[PDB]
Length: 113
Picture: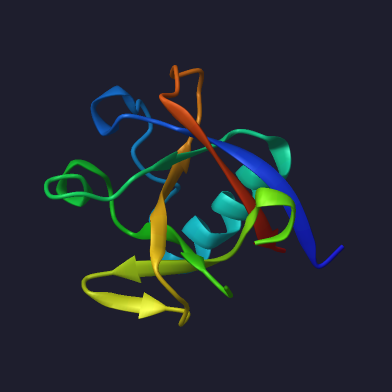
């Protein structure tokens, strides 16, 4: 399928144990997509002070369109030293590995895969 319905656990930035997906734009997009397929991906909501507490390159989920079955359609955009790889809508949050942190909420998305 071109899209997959996922329910992403929303993590507090100070709880996150693994603060990025790797060391290059291509690796972080690869690892993010693998962790989304495996159900091991968390979401941190971006506010003042969040991104400096995480590791670059960043992987964002961005709104791809204006929401089937309650799931916002999203795609991945990576960022490294102020340059984005991908073009999309509003940021829903930054993706991180999930390794058992307790979430505060779930974000229902339809991921363009």
